[PDB]
Image: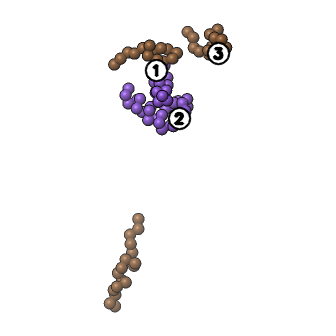
Amino acid sequence: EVYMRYRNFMVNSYRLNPNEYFSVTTARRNVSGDAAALFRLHKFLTKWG
Amino acid sequence: XXXXXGRXXXXXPXXXXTXXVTXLXXXXXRXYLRFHXXXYXXXXXXX
């Protein structure tokens, strides 16, 4: 359930403006959680387009 | 103007697959050893 929320936050806030690079720094700033978990999730998202 | 029932929504700007997303909320619509201590001239020197 919290995984789905992490992923939704990242993907939605990227799609609000698709030509601005989404950085893990903002994810770390807004969403509470382990930073390396968010790092791995961000990398996986970038992998699959 | 745009504030609704005590909510301050005023400070907002007002003016392959092609999925469509809702605006305002995006979602799909060194050293080498020296000789000593190296074990010679410690068994040697018949002089």
Q: What residue sits 48% from the left and 34% below the top?
A: A38
**Image quadrant where residue B3 sits:** top right
* Residue in front for this viewpoint, B45 or A49: A49
Q: From this viewpoint, which residue is outermost toward the front?
A: A1
Q: Is residue B37 above or below residue A23?
A: below
The tint of chain A in the picture is purple
Q: Which residue is mark 1?
A: A15
Q: Are marks 1 and 3 on the same chain?
A: no
Estimate the spatial distance between the alpha carbons at disc 2 and disc 1, rounded to whole Å.
Answer: 22 Å
Tag shown at residue A33: 2
* Residue in front for this viewpoint, A42 or B30: A42
- The chain displayed brown equals B
Q: From this viewpoint, which residue is outermost toward the bottom?
A: B47
Q: Chain of mark 3?
A: B
Q: Quarter holding the C terminus of chain A?
A: top left
What kind of residue is marked 1?
A: Arg
Residue B24 percent across, percent down from the top left:
52, 15
Q: Which numbered disc flags the more N-terminal residue, 2 or 1? A: 1
Q: What residue sits 35% from the left and 81% below the top?
A: B40
* Left/right of residue A23 with respect to residue B10 in the rendered view: left
Q: Residues within 10 Å of mark 2 (few under 14, many from 20)?
A: few
* Residue in front for this viewpoint, B36 or A42: A42
Can the viewer see residue B25?
yes
Nearer the observer, disc 3 or disc 2? 2
Please report contact status of discs 1 and 3: CB closer than 8 Å, yes or no.
no
Q: Residues within 10 Å of mark 1 (few under 14, many from 20)?
A: some
Q: Chain of mark 1?
A: A
Residue A18 percent across, percent down from the top left:
45, 21
Tag shown at residue B8: 3
What kind of residue is marked 2?
A: Gly
